[PDB]
Image: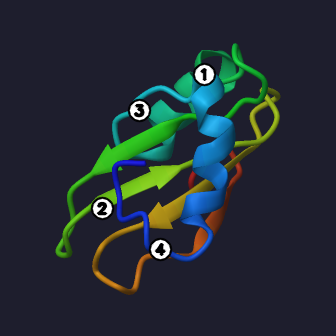
Amino acid sequence: DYDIPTTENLYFQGAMAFDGEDEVTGPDADRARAAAVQAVPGGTAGEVETETGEGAAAYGVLVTRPDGTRVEVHLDRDFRVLDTEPADGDGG
């Protein structure tokens, strides 16, 4: 929701974000802790992180199972951050 509403599929996840998708921090370390039970309180283990990169809105939204698995999506007005990333809880 923080990123640009004119992104790729980043405007689809936000929908389920109205449940319990709170604000994370940036890295997967925080998203895994929040999206775990912090974002799973609404309906699914998926929160929303907000980071700052070289672009504009270096934020992300992860949503999956509160078992450590999350789907962090890259959303940046950089016009190149509209993809997603399967959060393995470790963050590679």
Residue 53 in percent (x, y) is at 21, 66
User: Quick one: label 2 or label 4, which is nearer the N terminus?
Assistant: 4
**24 left or right of 37?**
left
**1 left or right of 51?**
right
Q: Which residue is mark 1?
A: 20
How far apart are the alpha carbons under marks 2 and 3?
12 Å
Could you say whether the residue bearing mark 3 is in a helix, strand or loop? loop
Residue drawn at x 45%, y 32% as measured from the top left:
30
Could you say whether the residue bearing mark 1 is in a helix, strand or loop? helix
Q: Nearer the viewer, residue 59 or 2?
A: 2
- Marking on residue 39: none
How far apart are the alpha carbons under marks 3 and 1?
12 Å
Residue drawn at x 75%, y 33% as measured from the top left:
68
Q: Please name the amino acid that badge 1 sits on.
A: Gly
Q: Residue furthest bottom?
A: 80
How far apart are the alpha carbons under marks 3 and 4?
20 Å
Residue 82 in percent (x, y) is at 50, 76
How far apart are the alpha carbons under marks 1 and 2?
21 Å
Could you say whether the residue bearing mark 4 is in a helix, strand or loop? loop
Residue 24 in percent (x, y) is at 41, 32
